[PDB]
Image 1 (cartoon, rainbow, N blue to C red):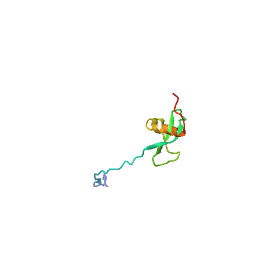
Image 2: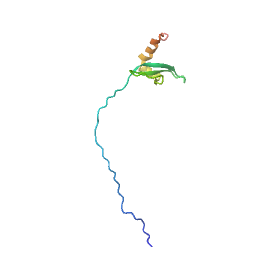
Image 3: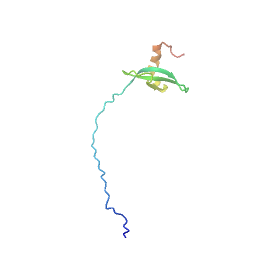
Length: 92
């Protein structure tokens, strides 16, 4: 009888990796807010909401909805949308 422990010789792995180094320039080609698409009130009772219309691209009512916070960035748009409607400015 033989009480041999194990019958293994050795164990070696590959672990081979190869990578290069580069870096090309990619044009941002980002979009910009052209004007408001639609207006919607916050059912939660927060503030006002307005959709952002991409210049050149006309999306449906499922466009991007921006919070009142965006008003500080696209104020001209928020007011413009109202001006086009024919509504007077807030009470003084």
